[PDB]
Structures are given as C-alpha cells and as structure tokens.
Image (tube, rainbow, N blue to C red):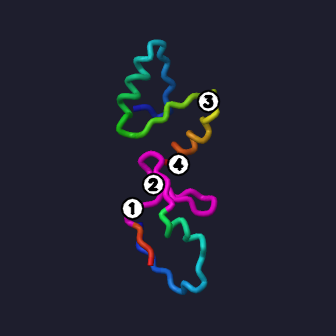
Amino acid sequence: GNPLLVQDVESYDPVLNPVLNREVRRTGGRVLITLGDQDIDLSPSFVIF
Amino acid sequence: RFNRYPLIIDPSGQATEFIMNEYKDRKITRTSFLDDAFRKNLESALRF
C-alpha cells in the first residue's frame, strides 16, 4: 500500500497493463489482481505515477 | 482453544451448524475431501 513513482516511461513495461486497467478480481473479501503468473492481493491505498 | 486443528465428530449435524453460525463473520467454504474442487479451495483459503 505504498505510493509508487516510476520514471523513464519510454522503456515501458507491459506488466503494468492489468494494474493500469484495474483488471481486478473480487473473490471473497480480498482484492486480487493477476500480473504474470503470480496472484497478488491489492491494497486499497495504492497509487502509481 | 485448540492447538492442533480439530476433528469434529457429529452424527447430529449440530456441531456443523454451530461452527457455520459461529465462524460466519469470516468466509467459510464448506468443502469435502472427495470434492474435485478441494485443492483450489484449500490453496485459496491458505493464501487468504
């Protein structure tokens, strides 16, 4: 749940696509976003720049 | 107050009803050992 600031967008990493698209699963009370193969619980207090 | 995970023996089903009504604030998936959708449920519960 930390703010993230990543510079040098020109070498963009397309692993950030579900994060930017908010492709989120809400199974149960948890909040899930799947990047790559790992499934990561998504905290509400996350921002990226 | 268990340390090792319990094994409830209940022919009547009253213990099952009690534990479902008791741990209802959290999320319970009542699985079974012969259910095909058991390993996935166990892994989800273990992670969550």
Q: Mark on residue B38? A: none
Q: What residue did someone put label 2 on?
A: A31
Q: What residue did someone put label 4 on?
A: B47
N-terminal label among 1 and 2: 2
Relative image position of residue A40 (x, y in whole percent): 53, 58
Q: What residue did someone put label 1 on?
A: A44
* Front disc: 2 or 4: 2
Residue at position x 49%, y 58% in the image:
A24
Q: Viewer-proximal residue, B38 or A20? A: A20
Q: Is residue B38 magenta?
A: no
Q: Which amino acid does label 4 sit on?
A: Arg
Chain letter for mark 4: B
Q: What residue did someone put label 3 on?
A: B35
Look at the image and tell me in which quarter the C terminus of chain A lies.
bottom left
Residue at position x 60%, y 84% in the image:
A11
Kindly state the secondary structure of the residue where label 3 is placed. Answer: loop
Q: Does the magenta stretch include residue A35?
A: yes
Q: Are marks 1 and 2 in contact (CB under 8 Å)?
A: yes
Chain letter for mark 1: A
Kindly state the secondary structure of the residue where label 2 is placed. Answer: loop
Q: Do the residues labelled 3 and 1 touch (CB within 8 Å)?
A: no
Start-end of magenta stretch = A23-45
